[PDB]
Image (spheres, coloured by chain):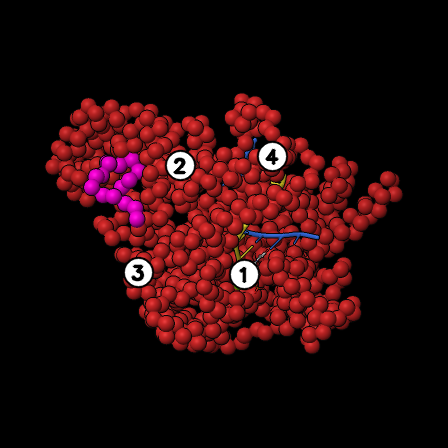
Chain colours: A red, B yellow, C blue
Amino acid sequence: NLLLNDYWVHNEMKAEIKMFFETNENKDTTYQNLWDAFKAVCRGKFIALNAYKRKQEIKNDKGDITTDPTEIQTTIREYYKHLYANKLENLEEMDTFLDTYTLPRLNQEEVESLNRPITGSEIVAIINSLPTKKSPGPDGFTAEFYQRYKEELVPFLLKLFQSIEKEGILPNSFYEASIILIPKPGRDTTKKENFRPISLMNIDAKILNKILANRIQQHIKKLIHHDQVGFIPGMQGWFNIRKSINVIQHINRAKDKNHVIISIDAEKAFDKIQQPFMLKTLNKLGIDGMYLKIIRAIYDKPTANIILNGQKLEAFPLKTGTRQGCPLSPLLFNIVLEVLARAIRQEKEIKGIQLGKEEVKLSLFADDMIVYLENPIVSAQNLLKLISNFSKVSGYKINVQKSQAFLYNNNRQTESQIMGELPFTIASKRIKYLGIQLTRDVKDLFKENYKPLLKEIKEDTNKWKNIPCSWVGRINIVKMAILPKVIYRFNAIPIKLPMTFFTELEKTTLKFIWNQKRARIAKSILSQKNKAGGITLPDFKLYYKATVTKTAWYWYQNRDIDQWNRTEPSEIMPHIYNYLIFDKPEKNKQWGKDSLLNKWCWENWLAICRKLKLDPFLTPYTKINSRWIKDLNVKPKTIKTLEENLGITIQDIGVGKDFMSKTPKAMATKDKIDKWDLIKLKSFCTAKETTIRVNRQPTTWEKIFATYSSDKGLISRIYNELKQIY
DNA sequence: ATTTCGC
RNA sequence: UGAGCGAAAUU
Ligand SMILES: Cc1cn([C@H]2C[C@H](O)[C@@H](COP(=O)(O)OP(=O)(O)OP(=O)(O)O)O2)c(=O)[nH]c1=O
Ligand SMILES: [Mg+2]
């Protein structure tokens, strides 16, 4: 990277590239071979410039533990070659699976936006957004080399990609990859299958894959369902954790227990996905033409060569499995797995347990497909046979050994057959789920989730006891090491906590900070902002309060994509959380008992609203669809008129003397609304209290939950407001 | 620019 | 060593 920061080398390489490009633009060869020669010449010139600058300045197949340098290379290579060799060929049988189920097609506009030619403005947003300080690819070039040689590379890379779209082939250098072996987290190193194969490609191939990945990500929301939250932008991990906790609670509270929960785990899902099946399901999804023409070309003859201890092992074909490290690979994998997800959802034999008017079948991630069943005796068998069919078609293999399960039955003898038939390893206490121990009983969540947290704190604080750093250094270590772990647990499980937990956590943190000494400066002063002179000592109580109150944003937005908020158990009238934020205070309705996660949010919302001394029941941000105006009889058709004409707030429709008449568009829309509704709305807005409640400047707190339509920094803003208030 | 987590 | 996607926090 130091060589690239030389101005003379910079100018020399610029001149060399210009010369090289304006020397042999003939017609005998193509742009791909020219680009390969370009890369080779640049490598040679870089080697020469570096020289000038320096002048100026495991167990084998039999199980035996072998240490022979040649034998280990021969066995790991054989294992990986056998892993990447089996390629399916029953293309006729593949389409039979697809034709039996429904898939979401794309309209003409979407494919048209998918097949638009690559322009010069679609590469500037990719090269600049390329992460730096990474490892070089097989060629040896770095991302910053493209980043800082941007002024001339773009309008010839444009022609190179033009050639790729027009003809349909890629340079032979775009297929090379490097595989490095890495030890997994918490596994024995003696087994050959315990390593993590990571792959690195060329930077230009990464740029092309990023362009395609963004082009398909613009519609990935329409493509796959909202159950899957892995790699989908705008979705968070706890979306499924909270849902699973709600299902656990519902099963626990049910008097008739005949349910089961299975945490299915795939066995090397990335490396076991058949390329022909992914191509055919991409074709079936309505994607055809230029996009398919290039995607098929990028997976024609992918090769990879392993590197161990700096050895250039010979390459072998990748006949199967999407090459990991590809920005486009997660999208294709999600598309392929969406077929299985929709097959499970559409199947009537698989019966999910109904949560009131909402029915939940299964939850998804990258691989952690957890599925909730009813009457396991036949539902588990149907799921297993469907997964077997999908396995034969596509190669998706499940590691039944690692897959755990929860059995919820009342009869002792009925459980015996269930354990005997299904090969699942039924767990009794805990199942790991994205770092959250899903307790079999809800009442043990605090015991098995936060006490081990505190134990790990008391261990890791013992680990960093002999670091000769400043107290600001220890504060920073706290901030970037211990805070995210607690915030993740709060986000996943924001339940009521006794004050002893916070007291002892604060005690441990303060012992960490002062290094077995007493406080030197006031805690309150250091807890203030940097402008006040403090170093902003974290306040875990405020973070907990912010995390608990964060659910009000999703309450107000009323997004249909999320289903976790509707899974709460309610033996009472239907959904209430929609008409709670900035709505009429409804009486004679007491939540709790059944609730585990939302009632505490409402209590904490009311407490902070009262501390703000502002009215939370009639605000300028009140929705038209609020209960404030449908308590009096109205017609549904009236609301959607001003919803699509003016907006959703109660301020824009009109209050006081501006009832549905404040702008020429509203003046022309006034007669559209029905008169019987108009006489009601008028009278409603004639009241002095309504006018003074609506016509005011909203505070920052209201703007946090109302005007913002993005979650990028909700906890930060809410915690800042809480810190200002408290 | 950096950190952590999930995969 | 050490790559990719997504999420969160500090500046
Ligand atoms: C953890 C991890 C996963 N991945 C990708 C590759 C994996 O196929 C995918 C999910 O991996 P996992 O399902 O977490 O691991 P695995 O299924 O291979 O475990 P096992 O060896 O027992 O079969 O995410 C990375 O690219 N980098 C990573 O660091
Ligand atoms: Mg797996």
Q: Which residues are magenta?
A: A579-593
Q: What is the chain letter for disc 1?
A: A
- The Cα atoms of the two marked residues, 1 and 3, are separated by 50 Å
Q: Amino acid at mark 3?
A: Ala
Rendered location of residue A211, percent (x, y): 55, 51
Evaluate if marks 1 and 2 touch, with contact meaning CB atoms under 8 Å apart: no
Q: Amino acid at mark 4?
A: Ile
Q: What is the chain letter for disc 4?
A: A
Does the magenta segment cover residue A228? no
- Ranked by sequence position, the earlier of labels 3 and 4 is 3
Task: State the residue position of label 1.
Answer: A295
Q: What is the chain letter for disc 3?
A: A
Evaluate if marks 3 and 4 touch, with contact meaning CB atoms under 8 Å apart: no
Does the magenta segment cover residue A589? yes
> Of helix, strand and loop, which one carries label 2?
loop
> Of helix, strand and loop, which one carries label 4?
helix
- The Cα atoms of the two marked residues, 1 and 2, are separated by 38 Å
Q: Which mark is residue A254?
A: 3
> Of helix, strand and loop, which one carries label 3?
loop
Q: Which mark is residue A708?
A: 2
- Ranked by sequence position, the earlier of labels 2 and 3 is 3
Q: Amino acid at mark 2?
A: Tyr
Q: What is the chain letter for disc 2?
A: A
A201 versus A599 height, above or below: below
| Marks 1, 4 in one chain | yes
**Towards the viewer: B4 or A501:** A501
- Left or right: A339, with A194 as reference point: left
Query: Is residue A232 in sight in this rendering?
Result: no
